[PDB]
Image (cartoon, rainbow over all chains, first blue to last red; front, side):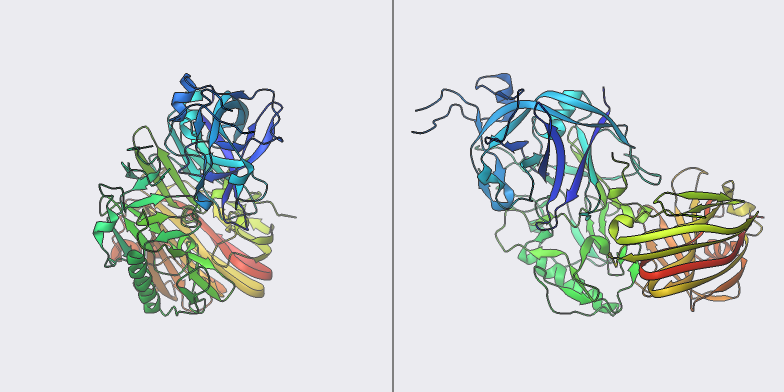
Length: 404
Length: 218
């Protein structure tokens, strides 16, 4: 019995998507998969190059078909139909699309962990996942065959492993900016150790409630909630000074508009025009206040700046920090420059927050770059999010796990 | 005889010398460290490196660290220190600092980090709330600039020299005593770590030659 599990992740350079690797099929093959933190399941391309002797269709009106979230039953191919075939709707969120999909079981194998190094390989003989057509791989990192869903369902990696191996329904995940080395996600229990000697545990992380959006943004089920991860930002501070925003937008409504969610599909943090204006203006305002000047706006970014008085620090460049103040005034997701800024070249630094129009379903969406080098723990059982802060502050990185 | 591994180490007298390339994943390049001379509470060494990429991200913290027992500030009479070094190489962005840590137990994770920067080269700078000095003290025969900032659940206090100090000598305890008297650090806290090292970001054909370094706890 393993206490936990560890998969590698790595940043694809073209797309800025986070890519992970599990083992699937008999004989085992290594599958690259795009990480979708919000996703509802593992779905893999099931074309003629999917050869396995341990694949099984999941039948409708079976225990495993209810678990999947399958609302319908049965299939009509073309030239006739099939009675009950456990159809679902695998989603590519990069291209806002959903094709139809058939639930199935096959062998999945990953590495176990004691939380400090790579353990012996362990296996889920009948791991439940979704087939999909090659077309749902549109605009996904080269080499990948599907998408790793980490959302809040029974059959998505974290709860399905949790269930398979009988450990706590939780996973930490530590994204990196490197296309170079391996980052990691760790399914199961704490404490996570990052070389040389940096221990991260539930005693160490900051905890905010994990909130449930009662209506789904995931807009493909009637009166079915979002399986995504939203947290409760009360205000934004830019170096001790509250930015003037509509605080009503921060709160999730009756219809499921507004609020803050975390995602791994968005490489930079999407800000609604109202919040975007205020955050950007104030960030510029304060940056000039320590003699950091504005330069041309490089794509895809709003604000960009000279590296002339930009001092290098351990925590990034010497720019004001953005503090997202959560449920209390003493609980804050701090964002230093390593998490806010993005080097274009030697001489220009841009702010890594993009504008997302108006009438977007969610007011704030925390993105990949702002997640990079933070240990972020999702506890589904007790409905909370714990976070480490910039791991650079302790002189480690998300790429310092002893992975093999 | 040197070492070039990410976690390669060396023990010499009172010290452990650390290559500690913790941010090598943030950039492209090389770093090699080695002992030149040691005896007891004194050491000599060098780290040659070239790093490019990640102009924001620290690639390593090559440091010599003293081996001692966690000790309360109110028991420390003096921490005598001598440091002489030289840096060759082009486009060097890096610092050279004493680096220490204060906990409330002789074991618990740290509450204060206190640094004394003998050099800030090519853009290097300390953690800061405002970006401005909180004091400009004169301590141990050097005019310093003091900054302060949050790091997780740790206040970081950094004393930076007004100009690059290739030769330094004095009582490092003074820096603690000053913080205890002027910034409300508890004299009861344990000193857990004492490290003198260099953190580079980017540069070419660099070499930090530490010609002598010596530190003690009395």
